[PDB]
Image (tube, rainbow over all chains, first blue to last red; front, side, top):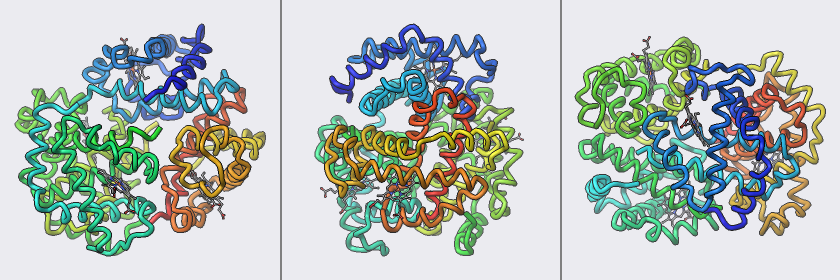
Length: 141
Length: 141
Length: 146
Length: 146
Ligand code: HEM
Ligand code: HEM
Ligand code: HEM
Ligand code: HEM
């Protein structure tokens, strides 16, 4: 469960990605594809070049959803409900891959905002990404 | 989430372990120690012999807790609350090990009740053991 | 890690009693019922909306047999499991696009099917030998992903 | 899997810029803050009730340095990582009783600390080279468990 302190920590680090949703979402994606190459089996129709239009457009969508989640961090299940359905019934991605992405998101914040991503804030952001992965996986069976 | 059908499936398979809580809990444990030997780092004070008094007494405790959980399968969090605390604050076992045990429990029911553990009932029991592992892990951070 | 002589004799002796067609059909059917989202890979086989469909789907039953017959050839290549599965590993990645986490999930289900069909042979130590086998088959099949 | 020449040059070139004491102290401190139950292993080091305590605990800071200095010797044994860590693997299992899942968790944290300290060198491909290194160090340290 996310505490009041966790929630303020996450809102503070996340306000630094403001204005950079496409830039940071595309990097997290490129990092996931390169460090965990098994995750490419879910994107066979994508051009995997650096900075490809597809990887940019999807990176933006993913980060935009995370932004909505931060703004509604009291009710994650109601905020991620449509996405939860989409992943369970159509895309059907194995739950283990949500940890790979979450890790790559931490890496991108560590590169762009190293001093902001302190040990206490890293712990809050790690919890938040688990809570988001858990909602995205909640309708699978 | 456990459905009405899942709940009836689990109550039915679990009523077959009645009268065998010590026998089956000790076997699940022996299986976990032998198939996933890394789990022994949590029991350095135990005699690891087959059918040791310690492995019997603990196997019984574990299965007894699972029995209470089946009888209160509507409110797992209120049924496993004290155990949840104990694992988070004292025993502090990494969450990944709860899947090893859950798997070993399925194996023991497959050996003693192969025809009862049908594919549909296997799916319900797998869900139930995940839901129990999730409650036991819920207070960790 | 190699297989010691004891581990090898557990694996070789039991495997010779296994009905590979029956067990293979059971393992794949259980995987699709216990983890329903894995039906994404087999929607070309026809009706799979529920467990009754899966168990009556003849193409699923056949695929489960050829999957377990292929896994069983590990038992005659115990020294060279990575090398024996390397082409199959590249097909999974390049042609079928199968997530490699599935190899460890099916391995765990195969252990439950072996336990139910051979309760008297599937002792604690026999189980530990198979759990190692299933681990190494999963890693060989995941190896050539890129 | 061996390291190709490109992977080796990413790992060797970056490692030579790393401040091992600073980074090692940071990685261990982050692990104990992000996963608080891991403090069970270090309760002989004194006060660790909160994050402020952990970061001011001198024995934790020293242990993080010697852990990362030992991991860094992988960089001069890239062909032989399993063999180089085999004694250390048995100590973790037999003497310290450390759950081997911790080796992959610390590996992931070390990647976040390297990213924060070397943002310009820690490119996508550099990251993929380190992720492989951290994977193989974790498996070597888990190897001798029994
Ligand atoms: C925080 C985690 C995630 C979030 C917030 C997220 C969010 C999204 C969103 C917003 C979309 C677009 C859906 C739409 O267009 O309506 C989507 C599509 C998709 N997601 Fe996820 N996702 C996450 C994790 C993952 C992971 C781990 C994978 C696979 C490894 C994945 C695979 C996909 C795929 C394949 C699509 C469709 C891509 C396409 O064809 O354009 N997602 N996701
Ligand atoms: C379904 C999963 C589990 C249940 C229901 C469960 C239940 C219990 C119970 C009832 C006890 C006794 C507590 C007491 O005496 O008040 C206990 C103790 C303990 N549990 Fe768990 N447990 C589970 C999973 C695990 C796992 C996976 C591990 C380690 C791999 C573990 C390690 C321990 C240990 C070390 C003790 C103390 C043992 C002793 O010193 O006698 N538990 N657990
Ligand atoms: C031990 C595990 C496995 C083994 C030994 C195995 C082996 C095989 C073999 C021998 C084939 C036939 C390849 C050919 O046509 O030349 C195959 C095909 C295939 N396997 Fe696997 N497999 C395994 C696990 C899985 C799992 C877990 C899945 C999915 C959940 C899967 C999905 C596929 C698919 C989709 C095909 C192609 C089916 C088709 O389109 O006809 N495999 N596998
Ligand atoms: C890459 C990962 C790791 C490496 C390379 C590493 C290396 C070492 C080394 C070199 C020592 C000193 C051994 C000696 O005295 O001869 C050590 C001790 C120890 N390590 Fe690790 N370690 C790693 C991960 C971990 C993790 C993740 C934990 C716990 C979370 C841990 C817990 C311990 C403990 C408890 C000791 C003994 C400390 C003491 O009582 O003084 N290690 N490790």
